[PDB]
Amino acid sequence: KMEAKIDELINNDPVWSSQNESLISKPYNHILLKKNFRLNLIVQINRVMNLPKDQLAIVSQIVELLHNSSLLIDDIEDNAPLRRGQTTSHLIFGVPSTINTANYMYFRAMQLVSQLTTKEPLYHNLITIFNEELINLHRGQGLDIYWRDFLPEIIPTQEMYLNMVMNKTGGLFRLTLRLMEALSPSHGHSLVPFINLLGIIYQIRDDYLNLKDFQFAEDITEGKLSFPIVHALNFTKTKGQTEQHNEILRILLLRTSDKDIKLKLIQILEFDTNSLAYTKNFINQLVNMIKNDNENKYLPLYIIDHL
Amino acid sequence: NKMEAKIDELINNDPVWSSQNESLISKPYNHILLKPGKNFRLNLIVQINRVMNLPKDQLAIVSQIVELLHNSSLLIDDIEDNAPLRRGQTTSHLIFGVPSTINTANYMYFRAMQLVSQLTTKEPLYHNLITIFNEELINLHRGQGLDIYWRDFLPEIIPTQEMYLNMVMNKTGGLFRLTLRLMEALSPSHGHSLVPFINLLGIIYQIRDDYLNLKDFQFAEDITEGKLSFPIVHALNFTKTKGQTEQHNEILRILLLRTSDKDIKLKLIQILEFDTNSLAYTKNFINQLVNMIKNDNENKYLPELLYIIDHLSEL
Ligand SMILES: CCCCC/C=C/CC(C/C=C/CCCCC)(P(=O)(O)O)P(=O)(O)O
Ligand SMILES: CCCCC/C=C/CC(C/C=C/CCCCC)(P(=O)(O)O)P(=O)(O)O
Ligand SMILES: [Mg+2]
Image (cartoon, rainbow over all chains, first blue to last red; front, side):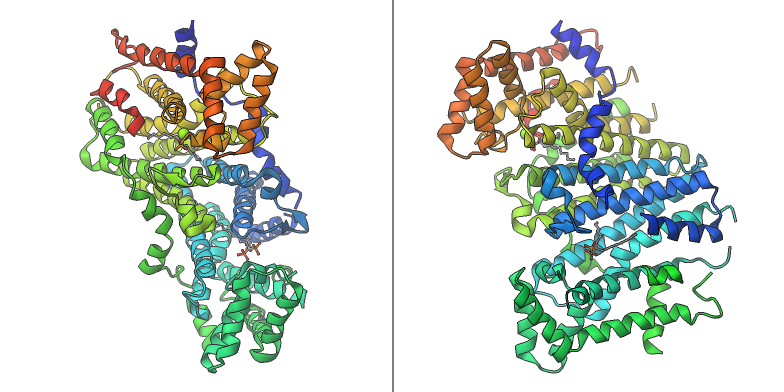
């Protein structure tokens, strides 16, 4: 009867219950409490693409799974205690379950791609898009983490920083857009260059506000090669400002939560390298590239301000 | 206008990525490759192929896919298990850090995925292969999710033998079925599906892995990890059934210590030895599974194969 139960088990598909499904979904469901704005960007873009609502909703579900899962992983990789003022998933469910659940969701997302179309040519394209951007997202993340964890072995320049962003942040943006463009039953030049720009603006502003809001500035504690930090390191290098250059490095290397020390790094950025003003300006120019796109080379606005 | 011009160029092109960038993020992965077994996993594929007859070009690609998935799963697994060693060498996360190791492992899941396109140009087949890839990776993560949940939230859920076996069908069964199913789908030919057989192989493999981790010690790292192993699942249900309250609680207590103390680990092992007879039970359960194949004279499960089964511990 032992052998009989084994026969039954190996001839059936692996058993999995809704109760099991809920257990593994816990770390994921916790971050859901943190979507209205990203859905808006998708609805807006769909005016140019025109996917039928149902197909649109699946793209949205795919994009929500990747977004949320990648943030669960990112918070573990950044040792972040909070995400939108709430305790991070891994601190509640543990790093092990959270890594597994986030990765599980990548593949659930991958499965939804199959429900976008039954046309084999188009399907293959969609998987190829998914695959390529997840690959880019990972390269970008990998390089960002490498710079941070091997500091001070490599100090990126602005150009290296911008390529890392095109991979990382650009991956998620282009994935949503490229899927939508491949599905369009319609719509002008591709909006990829435009979504790339949005992604870059999004990341620099994210780096900028992390330091500006403090002026918690968790990016400092993390040791991240942020856009303002990249500017300051290369500024001090260039001007031969040895002590300042080394002091930025020292603070980043402390992995500090000390408010006083964080403020000091901010003092260097405000008074010595003027990196926060330089970033504010850099962002404004990226944005004016669109505000001033009268001939619609990028455009097919409100979203670019609430990015 | 030079900035705009550079920005315009940057955004109208694919993201820049160098071979140098590629080597820096491959560190955690290149490191686990320095571990053996590759030959043995290849040996199983080779033997299975005597049935499937995939051309060597294709078989090579199937093997690259499975190897990437295998090694990446292990990198993640060692982080999830807080493992300090793997095949006698330091785990990657301890060298390059957990952050880089998670990213790299996940990166390789997608490289493995990308490779599936190199198996065929036939779109219906392509669709079938990716579906197989997607399904078993979903199964693998479900199984791993349960194994980890049971362990990290113990005693919230004490799995029974049946729950354990289902978890294994999903987790270890996932990787064994992935390889086999890809091959069955690519076969140009050859008898009943080998899925039941490959599930049994995954099950013998897992319970034997659990078994040997304790028997070899009798470093029993599974005890330090607090894993709900086959012998541990038997012990916990055996003691509850027989009303051995103190022994049932002490097993849970030792698991929850996450201890490396050798005497404490030996104490737990000897409890399973003389008190619950979990080592004997497991050993016999393994032999019974193996006998289901060795006594498969009607080739119900079966299509060098037995050789594998005996050196299964080295895949
Ligand atoms: C392979 C994992 C990729 C994770 C990418 C996420 C990064 C998160 C950040 C912000 C990125 C947000 C991307 C939003 C994309 C919306 C579609 P954070 O500030 O929330 O930590 P950062 O670590 O790059 O700064
Ligand atoms: C999503 C990650 C799945 C990881 C599955 C791997 C588990 C590893 C083990 C062994 C599993 C091996 C899978 C079969 C390999 C066949 C070549 P270990 O002993 O190396 O830690 P276990 O945690 O199941 O015991
Ligand atoms: Mg094991």
